[PDB]
Image (cartoon, coloured by chain):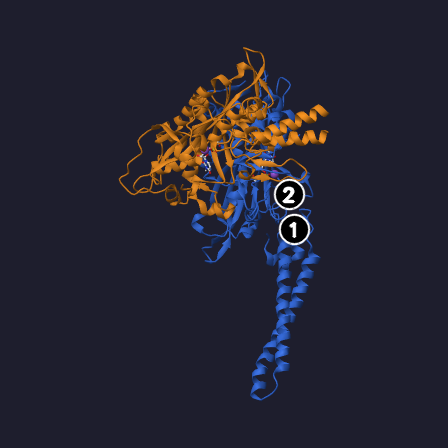
Chain colours: A blue, B orange
Amino acid sequence: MLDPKLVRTQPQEVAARLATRGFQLDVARIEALEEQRKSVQTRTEQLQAERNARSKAIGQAKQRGEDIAPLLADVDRMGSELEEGKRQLDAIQGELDAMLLGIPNLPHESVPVGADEDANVEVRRWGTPKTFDFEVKDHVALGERHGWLDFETAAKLSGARFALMRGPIARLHRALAQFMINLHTAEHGYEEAYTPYLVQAPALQGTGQLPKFEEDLFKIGRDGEADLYLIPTAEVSLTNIVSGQILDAKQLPLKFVAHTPCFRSEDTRGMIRQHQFDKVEMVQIVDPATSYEALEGLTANAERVLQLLELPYRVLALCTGDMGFGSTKTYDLEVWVPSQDKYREISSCSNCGDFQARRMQARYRNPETGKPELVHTLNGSGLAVGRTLVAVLENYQQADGSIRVPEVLKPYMAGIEVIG
Amino acid sequence: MLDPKLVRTQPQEVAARLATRGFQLDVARIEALEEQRKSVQTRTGKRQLDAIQGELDAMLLGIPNLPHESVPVGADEDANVEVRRWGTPKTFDFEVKDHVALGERHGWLDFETAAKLSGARFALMRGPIARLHRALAQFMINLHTAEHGYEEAYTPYLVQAPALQGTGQLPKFEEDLFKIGRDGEADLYLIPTAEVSLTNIVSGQILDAKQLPLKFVAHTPCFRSERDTRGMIRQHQFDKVEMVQIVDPATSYEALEGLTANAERVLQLLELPYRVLALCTGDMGFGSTKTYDLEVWVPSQDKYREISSCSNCGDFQARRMQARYRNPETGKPELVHTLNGSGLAVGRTLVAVLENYQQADGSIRVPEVLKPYMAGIEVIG
Ligand SMILES: Cn1c(=O)ccn([C@@H]2O[C@H](COS(=O)(=O)NC(=O)[C@@H](N)CO)[C@@H](O)[C@H]2O)c1=O
Ligand SMILES: Cn1c(=O)ccn([C@@H]2O[C@H](COS(=O)(=O)NC(=O)[C@@H](N)CO)[C@@H](O)[C@H]2O)c1=O
Ligand code: NA
Ligand code: NA
């Protein structure tokens, strides 16, 4: 949610900033609703003035021994219209709120203005994509060899876009997730958390997936119970820890890390696109003055995972036309994928500003004013575990089809140094 | 599903054995349907044959497993037999606190934030308690893979109906599952246990005799919409480290003893006193022939509480899955036997760790085997 006062009073300036995202604000409808509101409010004011006078004129008519029936009938009619005037103003405000819940965030001034994906800038890249002396295999060819990565058995259980891992590939996947959590808790100042993987609608509305992106979620419809949704990311559960709270300035920043499955009902082959995937999520609840510096740190934390695994990657600053709904500024990390001869997305790191904090009423008590003020929220993958496994399998492949274990993962691989 | 030959050749004995579970086998309806199929065959139309076949198959999928002759005969939980114990429950020199009071002290176990997010029967864990939960699950999976011969697996947590019918949750227990209704697609169900995904790896296959035993281990969330039940004891979501075995039918009752010892080892290494209960015929799970429950000591309750269920399913799930192996003696593809057991339910291990390891000041001492996973933390709070 944007600032309601800003959208209602400056719809033209808000529309112009939003147009950079390709989003066309319904300025004609905001102004029409605002014209209707002003018209009803002026009618209720004139009626309040008329009814109050008539209601007190009954007292005076009584003192004169006069008939009060014409006056009571006037007051009663006026009262009934004021009650409708309230219903009209409530239904106008109701329509305006429903509309404001579907508006994407305002891009920060520093975001490059672009109409599409081609206006995204490379910020920097790290490491050098390996030149192989043999024909590179993809992660599907590599992992299927001994049945350690099995899409057929997963299709037999659950249908398309699911995976089954066994033996050393399953251990390598767990090693990756354990390495990420241990790194963020030991070196990057994040507090570990275990969260529900099923949330009710209010949590998803707090982070921006609801009301607009319901069709992308798996829903559990329940009889006489509030429906449950499978989390698309631990961002939903972690960010909402602070909903409806006034935090002390001393408690900021709150930094959370969670390793959870992620469920989405939205080449893309093998493990690139899945209905379920593990992701180690980083979430920060910060002082608004520090959120853009916090984003730089958050991005460096996700990068550190790739540097430690020695995986060549690239950092992209997303343009205005290529951002997520609730983001003011995003950096995408893209890992080198040898079988594709390109870098592919492995993490998105965003500053949401006060957009999610507004929806969930997550606040802090400002020290200067003493007044409760909205916090800023940030989130970032550090990393999507299945995609890192794809990167590990492909970048560490040997000529015989075996896989070298990355150095930082050997303590988790129980003596295994080469897979197959 | 039960052997169709046994149901036909020995109806009275199969019915008398099932009656020890409190299940009344409808021999009359089964044999009346068999007579109708035989009469319709001698005349052959397709409508009446498919209706009789659909009726018979639906009945057949509703019959629980035959209890093994070594299973104590009883009507309820009070007839379950304690077969052994391990360890001495601790005598505390202060008033014992439950895991809820222990965990809630610094916000590290938070039922209120979880309720705000998801409603009742959910949990949120933070900092050293979340780290201890993760340490427990890592310990269990590292133990089973390194010492007990189990191959690790990452599985889907959403399955379609045939996998649940393969292990016995469907058709009879649909109400206990969280279903995802999918428009113009097969509905998905959240897994109640990794037993569903692990056991079904071998469905529709003829394995090699040399491939047996197949021993799988997985750490997964478990989702169910179903004595003291406070906090993490009962949840809609909980983590469980599951052990599954696909074995030669001749070895399955020795394999159950080995599976039960694997689960027990986690409790021994954590130094958590417990007891082993041989479930009676009237307290057994639908798909089981024989079950041992592990019940860990819970100081706040002054009693042992269930933390694991180890079962031999015989050929029951194999029949539903058509999971076979090529018999080296005969040459014929024969049904395999299947087994599963918790090693362990992670949330309930955490309850047991918090309570048994608590100290006078409300702090919790970290179990010895968990210290390598706790980043220097030896005392929680
Ligand atoms: C397997 N798989 C998918 O099918 C889809 C996405 N991803 C990775 O997940 C990362 C984070 O997803 S996101 O871009 O929608 N952003 C978030 O979820 C925020 N909570 C920040 O993480 C993407 O960068 C993909 O690499 C998959 O792995
Ligand atoms: C939190 N919680 C529950 O809410 C319910 C059960 N349990 C434990 O899970 C163990 C295994 O569940 S079971 O008995 O249904 N058996 C199986 O699922 C098999 N696949 C073997 O694991 C129970 O023993 C409870 O201790 C919870 O922890
Ligand atoms: Na992205
Ligand atoms: Na049980």
User: Are the residues flagged by discs 2 and 1 in contact, CB closer than 8 Å?
Assistant: no
Marks 2 and 1: same chain?
A: yes
Q: Position of residue A262 (x, y in %)?
A: 56, 37
Q: Is residue A174 visible?
A: yes
Determine the image quadrant of residue B59. Answer: top right
Residue position for label 1: A17
Residue position for label 2: A215
| Rendered position, A194 above or below A417 | below
Determine the image quadrant of residue A292. Answer: top right
Depth order, front residue of A20/B257: B257
Depth order, front residue of B344/B4: B4
Tell me the distance, in whole angstroms, between the alpha carbons under discs 2 and 1.
Answer: 27 Å
Return the mark for residue A115: none
Q: Position of residue A335 (x, y in %)?
A: 59, 31
Chain that bears disc 1: A
Q: Position of residue A261 (x, y in %)?
A: 54, 35
Q: Secondary structure at mark 1?
A: helix
Q: Secondary structure at mark 2?
A: helix
Q: In the current view of this chain or complex, which residue is farthest to the bottom?
A: A64
Q: Is mark 1 within 8 Å of ligand 3?
A: no
Q: In the current view of this chain or complex, which residue is farthest to the left?
A: B93
Depth order, front residue of A49/B201: B201
| Rendered position, B243 above or below B76 | above
Ligand 1 shown in quarter: top right
Q: Amino acid at mark 1?
A: Arg
Residue at (41, 38) in percent of width and height: B129
Q: Amino acid at mark 2?
A: Glu
Chain that bears disc 2: A
| CA neighbours of label 1 inside 10 A, class few (<14), some (14 to 19), many (20+) | many
